[PDB]
Image (tube, rainbow over all chains, first blue to last red; front, side):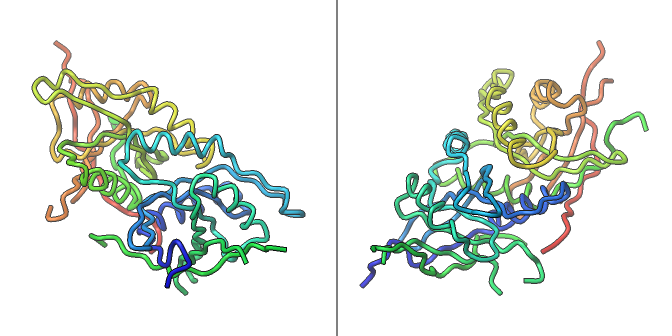
Length: 161
Length: 158
């Protein structure tokens, strides 16, 4: 009875640790704002598996966030680089450090859909003193509007604390 | 201190980056060791290894003086890194050993192009197996070999 492409997202520690670092790592240079990135992983019985991830340069106007830019040439290259090394991981969605959805995530997601028709947004909460750290979403099409529904997301890679 | 570095702090990311990258390409009959670049910061002779990317690398299993590491890739990939991550620098390289290889001295020499005090870190990928073993090439005709540098893991938070 599944009208939805994905119904669960398993975000691996790497990713969460990837993003958290990437966030704080660029904070020592007065990083004020949220980070945006791409997710790479595999697909199963509607379980999306998010194995790996890279950051992409992204800007948005803090006064009208319909003014934003995400560098698709970068993402395409960087993903190209990834294929040269890591076996078949695919662009499976994207991420950003929220902590909440943004007015423009729907539009950002639309760009991403170019690379994965069932892109899944995962909002990775970067704050340490902060419920479950990932919150996956996926754009549903409800004139004909568009909005993000919640998809179950938990963390869980095999082997070693 | 006649030595550039005397300690290497390898962060969980790296260790987890590499281990994954290793096993992640194992599901496709990965037979061999992985080689890569380390990115990080420098202090009071403590090298801090914050981040790392894999580079395509091949070596002949019958004469490992026949090997190749793709420097165009590393330069590019690093280029991409600067575009995002703040000042991390190429600080050495890594490979999944588990032991030193005949050619690491040569591979290191290529790397020295990008970091005159490159530090090799052998990241042991096996679970039933300290997981990092940093080295640095010392120049002892005038030979060249790797000395051990203290390496531990330790990033702040969760």
